[PDB]
Structures are given as C-alpha cells and as structure tokens.
Amino acid sequence: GTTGVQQALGALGDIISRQQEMNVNNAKLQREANTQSYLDQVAASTLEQLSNADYRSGLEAQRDAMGMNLDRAATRDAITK
Amino acid sequence: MAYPYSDMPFGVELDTSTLGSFGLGGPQTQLQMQMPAVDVNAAASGSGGFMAGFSNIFSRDSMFGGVAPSGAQTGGWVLPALGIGQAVFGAIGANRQQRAARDQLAESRRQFDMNYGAQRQSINTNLEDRQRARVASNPTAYESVDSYMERNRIR
Amino acid sequence: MAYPYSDMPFGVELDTSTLGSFGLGGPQTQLQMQMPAVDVNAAASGSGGFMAGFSNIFSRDSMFGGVAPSGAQTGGWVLPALGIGQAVFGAIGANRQQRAARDQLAESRRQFDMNYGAQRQSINTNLEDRQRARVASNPTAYESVDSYMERNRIR
Amino acid sequence: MAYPYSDMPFGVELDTSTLGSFGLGGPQTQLQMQMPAVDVNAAASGSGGFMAGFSNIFSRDSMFGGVAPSGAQTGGWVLPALGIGQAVFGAIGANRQQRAARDQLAESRRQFDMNYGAQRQSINTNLEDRQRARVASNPTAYESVDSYMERNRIR
C-alpha cells in the first residue's frame, strides 16, 4: 500500500517536467518571433524616413521597450546596414 | 463558521481510523445520494459558471494536442489523464496486495487458534472422564472434581 | 529558562525509547488539541507576520513554474513537494515492512512457547496421575508425592 | 426521459457488483440477440449514414501508412490497433492471474474447514459412543445424554 505510491508520485511529477520543457521551447520561438517582427519594421522603411532623425528615434525607442525579450545582437546597427 | 452545514457529525463518525477494514481500504460508509438536478443547466447556474453546454470542443487538437507550423505546439489533456489513472491504479494495486497479505496472515492465525481450541477441549474432556473414575471409586481417599478442575485444568 | 512552559514533563514521559511499540513506530501518545483560533487573522497576528490572507497566489507560475522569453526559468514548489512526499512514504513503507517482520517473528515465538506449555501441562498431568497409583497402593514401601513433584517434575 | 427504452431494468439487475463471478471477470449474463438488419443496406440507411459500404479502400497505404517524396508521412491504423490489443490482453492476463490466486486461496480455506469438519464429526462420534456406556450402565448414578450433548460437544 505504501510502496506503489512512489511510482504514482513519479508519474504525477514527470508530466509537469515535460510541460515545462515544451514551455521553454515555446518561449524561445516567441523570442525569435519578436526579433523578426521588429526587424521587418526597419526593413520596410524608405531611406528618406531613416535619414530623418525623428522617425528613427521612435523606431529604436520601440526597441528599448521590449527588454531582453528581443535578441539584442542582430537588432543593433540594423538601421545603418 | 457562519455556514456550519452538517459536516461536524461526519467528522465525528470518521474519528481518526486509517485505511483498512474490508472495503479495499475504506468501504462505502455513506449512502448513495440522488442527483442534485436532472438538467445540467450550465452547472450550478451562476454558481457554476462553466462551459459544459457552451464549449462543445469536439476537436482532436484539445484531446490529442496539435502543432501549428513554425513550432509552438500544445499538449492535450489525454496524456495527463492517462498518467493520473496510472498512478491511481498503481496505488490501488499496492493497497490490494497489502490487504491480501494481511488477510492471509490473519487467516493462518485463526486456523492455529481454532486448532488449539479444539485440542484443548478434547484434552479437558479426556481429563474429566479420567478423573470421573477417581472421584467415583473412593471419594474419601481421593480428591474432588473442583480441585482437579481448578489446579490441573488446561486453559 | 525564561519560558520553561511545560515541555519538561513531556520530555520525562518520552524518556529514551526508540521507534516500535504498535503505532507504526510511535503511537498517538498525546491527546488531540483544539485549534488556537477559529479565524486565521493572518497567522498569529504580529507574531505570525505571514501572507496567508495576503498572497493569494492562485497562479500556475507559482505552483507549476514558468519560463519567460529569453530563458530565465523559475521552478514551482510542486516538484519539491512531490519529492518530499515520495521520501516520507518510502520511509513509512520500510518501517511498515520491518514492523510486519517483527510481528511475524513474535507470532512464531508465541506459537512455539504456547505449544510447549500445553505439552508441559499434559506431561505433568500424565506423570502425576501415574504416580497416584504408586502412592495409593503401598505408601510405606513407595515414595511420597513431594519427592516426585519436586525432583522429576516438568519445568 | 424522451426515449426511456428499457435500460432501467437492466441497470436494476446490474445493481453495483464489481468484477469477478466466474466468467473470467463478468459472465454472459445477457442472451445472444438476433441480427438487427437482414442486409447491410449501408448501415441503418439514413439513420446510419456510414461510408463503410462504399469505402472499399483495399489499399496498403491506409493500413500500413505511407510516405510520399519530400517527407510528409502518414501512419496507418494497424500500429494503434496492435497497441490497443496489447493493452487489452495484458489487462486480461492480470485479471486471470488475480482470479487464479483467489481461487487457490479459497481452495486452501475450503480444505482446512472441511478437514476440521470431518475431524469434529469423528470426535463427536467417539464422544457419544464413549458416553453410551456411561448412560446405559448406571443411568441413575451417572449423567444424562443431554448434559454432554450440549456441554462436552465439539463445535
């Protein structure tokens, strides 16, 4: 009676581990989506707009609102490139 | 408590007994109670507030999960349900095995005690009928029945 | 000390006995105690200083953990709780098995000792009922009851 | 309800008995019913509305699956069917083993009880034929039959 409950607890506790791993994968994909979504905005802007130093101020202020949820190594120097 | 209801007598009846007895570790002590309502009426109306008659899922994506393109998958509740059932049935099996072992041991003890009782009664009968001759032949020169029955009598 | 309370008699009663007896390695020696207060009142008011009525987590992130984008995971307490329960129940099962083995050995002890006692009384009865004839036929030329009952009597 | 049919007497007859009895965990309590329809008629015509009558798949891809170029593979139902059969037969085997163990235990109990009954009858017979001489020789100076027959009678 008290010996089989260990397997019960293990089988109750492994499923949440699998759920956590799936959550990790989903979070990583969400971060990638955020990065690409930002990069599209700078990619779809005309040169005259990026030259003016009021459009780019807001454009890179939208980058400082998202924190580390947006890969900050492929979205820096994007405007210059 | 503002709403005592009637759980106090139930708790009093429960006392502090642990699992065992005869009903696979707790029999159906209580009595079957009729359904609160024939119609679902969306659970307990306002109190319930569920989607029993509103959800109507009927989709494999919820039972068995599903993955849209670009990853981002979701798991259904079928796997957790199977895991929970597995755990419960394993616990029930362990309890059943423990109960069977206890039974067997108690049964063997019962047989030994009953055999001893039968043999003891037979021995007492033999002693009584052997002492009958002594108390019937020469009562004056021999002891009485009470002395043998209270001094050389098998428990 | 400053606050002796009444733990000295409890410690005196405990003495230094180890696990065993009959209550799965220590029965309910003490008596049931009523709740200090019906209302939680945020634990023991100032003494408690907890968030029992303030936290109200009700959040899967606390029970089941959660991972924000860019890693930085946090684990819930459900897994530690399950591990602690597993450990406790395994220890309880081991104690139960040890107790069952001890009980079986004690039952065998009782079996054999009881059977020997029964046979002992039977043999002693046989000897003394045989000796009645010797001491009643020719008391002068034969020995007394005391000699046989103290020299060739069964222990 | 709207269509009560006749399930109520069946439910009453079932009562709340669990698995067991003699038919490998539930015998054929009901009887063999006749065929519902003479011809397939595409299941129950409009009521059925099935496609098995016109499916005629006869295709290995549906049974054992198949993969087109560039991945995009589909699995057939044969593997799930085999898994389901495996599970069902494992459960049946476990039930059979439990039933066999119960049988064996019941047989042992019957053996012991029946041996005790035979021995008790023999001992009672010995007793009444032994007391027959006592009650036939000197009835006045000895006891009556009933005294022993409900005082010194083996249960």
Image (cartoon, coloured by chain):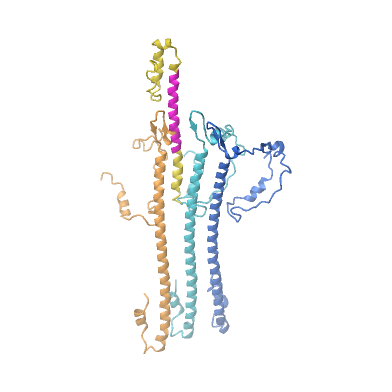
Chain colours: A yellow, B cyan, C orange, D blue
In which quadrant will I find the N terminus of chain D? top right
Dominant SS type (magenta): helix
Residue A20 percent across, percent down from the top left = 44, 35
Which residue is found at the position 56% from the left and 51% from the top? Answer: D92
In the orientation shown, which residue stands out farthest toward the right? D38
Q: What stretch is highlighted in magenta?
A: A17-40
Q: Which of B105 and A33 is in front in this view?
A: A33
Residue C67 percent across, percent down from the top left = 41, 31
Please tell me whether residue C121 is drawn above or below residue D58 in the rendered image: below
Residue C117 percent across, percent down from the top left = 41, 71
Please tell me whether residue D26 is drawn above or below residue A62 in the rendered image: below
Q: Magenta span has A25?
A: yes
Please tell me whether residue B63 is drawn above or below residue C27 in the rendered image: above
Please tell me whether residue A27 is drawn above or below residue B96 in the rendered image: above
In which quadrant will I find the C terminus of chain D? bottom right
Which residue is found at the position 60% from the left and 52% from the top? Answer: D26
Question: Number of callouts in the render?
Answer: 0
Q: Which of A19 and B53 is in front in this view?
A: A19
Question: Viewed as shown, does residue B146 lie left or right of D154?
Answer: left
Which residue is found at the position 56% from the left and 84% from the top? Answer: D137
| Quadrant in the rendering for residue D133 | bottom right
In the orientation shown, which residue stands out farthest toward the left? C1
Question: Viewed as shown, does residue C130 lie left or right of D59?
Answer: left
Q: Can residue D106 be seen in this view?
A: yes
Residue B103 percent across, percent down from the top left = 49, 58
Q: Is residue C58 visible?
A: no
Q: Which of C128 and C64 is in front in this view?
A: C64
